Amino acid sequence: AGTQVADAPQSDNTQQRHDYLGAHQAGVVTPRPAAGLLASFDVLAEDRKELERLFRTLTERIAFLTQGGPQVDPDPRLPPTGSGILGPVVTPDALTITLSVGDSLFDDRFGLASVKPRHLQRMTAFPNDALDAALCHGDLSIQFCANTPDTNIHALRDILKNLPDLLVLLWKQEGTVPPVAHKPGTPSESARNFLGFRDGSANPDSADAREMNRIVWLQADSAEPAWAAGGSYQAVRIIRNFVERWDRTPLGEQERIMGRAKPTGAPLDGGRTEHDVPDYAVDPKGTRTPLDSHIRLANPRTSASQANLILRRPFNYSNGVTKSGQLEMGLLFIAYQADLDAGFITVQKRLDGEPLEEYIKPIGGGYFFTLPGITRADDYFGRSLLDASAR
Ligand code: HEM
């Protein structure tokens, strides 16, 4: 293959396509691809008209970018239609774009406060946090997922190109997960995090609409405002890993901080695969699965704890080198739940003081409400929020 050194890699994955219409936005129960980008913005709109145009315009960009197609530049004296990163024919590359609104959007600016989702709130500092003020909150989060980082970056460029007057980017975190070798005829396997552990084994069934309806998605008739039906609460946490320290920790200690076997992801009390679960009823004292191990604290597997299940959808992030010359990398923790208080906050409240904290440090993120989907291309994300607020 007389391939030139700068030839672009070729991949059949570029034409994969996820629909952006539905009862829900894509990117929540959609299978997580190899590349991710979570960006936070402040809305610069000064009124309900400009906020409507922002919602209409984001929708328009989502429809094109996630489905792809030709991009014609109108005239040489004008800026080009887009950045051109994906060529004159934009490829979707399995891109999903998920829109979520922060607590701060429901201030006095737009007259939405009286229909704010009832668990929506500003993220507050947990005891092991070292929050960078510049990495927290935002009027609007946008989660981009695609097969390769250039597709999310291209989507980011396009949105900022078309809304530089209504959006200011505040902070962003890109991330990835390591793909595994194909192997048809084997159970699918959970991606690893940068601590080298399988990450997602005990997620609830993302392919089970009944399970998602009671764990992830807001339901119509409930204590929530009716417009918010089909949305979800989104918790984002930028979590440093002190990796050099971790890599100097004995394997057996890594396994009892996490409470799973490292190479397999199996329970520490038996079972071969990562789909097995420990039996805490058998082990009340934590002699197989430590009481203070990460999983056992995150989910003690009591009947009461089934109210605190969450859907994790993380990426791994690599940001550079610190001043003591250590790798600036960690977890881009993203999680969805029908109830933010019973979910992420309760779980993190259980996790405070866990031994893992010796190796991790949340530095940023915030809480957002992922908006309901649209089934009608005449419709647009955020519309029901504007109408509900309009009584
Ligand atoms: C960088 C920090 C973290 C790492 C490396 C990490 C890693 C892991 C690993 C390896 C598992 C076991 C496999 C699995 O069931 O998915 C797990 C489980 C879990 N993690 Fe985390 N995690 C981190 C932070 C968090 C945080 C902040 C939460 C807060 C909500 C959380 C919630 C959970 C839950 C609910 C489970 C499932 C426990 C179970 O049902 O057995 N994790 N985590």
Image (spheres, rainbow, N blue to C red):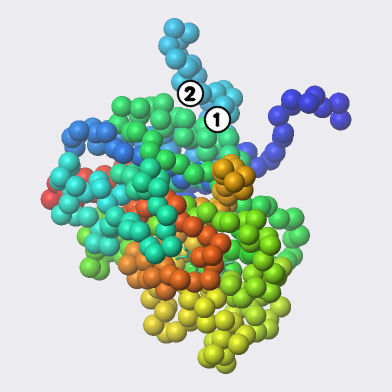
292, above or below 224, in the image: below
The 10 Å Cα crowd at callout 1, few under 14, some 14 to 19, many 20 or more, is: many
Is there a contact, CB below 8 Å, between mark 1 and mark 2?
yes
**Residue 149: x %, y % from top left:** 58, 39
| For marks 1 and 2 on the same chain, the one whose residue lies earlier in the sequence | 2
Q: Amino acid at mark 2?
A: Gly
Is residue 23 visible in the rendered image? The answer is: no
The kind of secondary structure element at disc 1 is: strand
Residue 199 or residue 59, whichever sits in front: 199
Q: Is residue 126 left or right of residue 14?
A: left
Which label sits on residue 90?
A: 1
Report if the beta carbon of the residue with label 2 is closer than 8 angstroms to ligand 1. Answer: no
- Residue 150 vs 388, above or below: the answer is above
The vertical placement of 209 against 94, above or below, is below
Query: Where residue 257 appears, x then y in whole percent?
Result: 58, 72
The picture places residue 286, in percent across and down from the top left corner, at: 56, 86
Residue visible at 68% across and 83% down in the picture: 270
Q: CA distance from mark 1 to mark 2?
A: 10 Å
In this view, the residue farthest toward the left is 391
**Residue 341 pos. (x, y %):** 32, 67
Q: Residue at x 55, y 23 (%)?
A: 84
Q: Which residue lies under the disc numbered 2?
A: 82
Q: Return the residue nearer the eye: 357 or 101.
A: 357
- Which quadrant of the figure has residue 159? top left
Give the camera-side residue of 290 and 152.
290
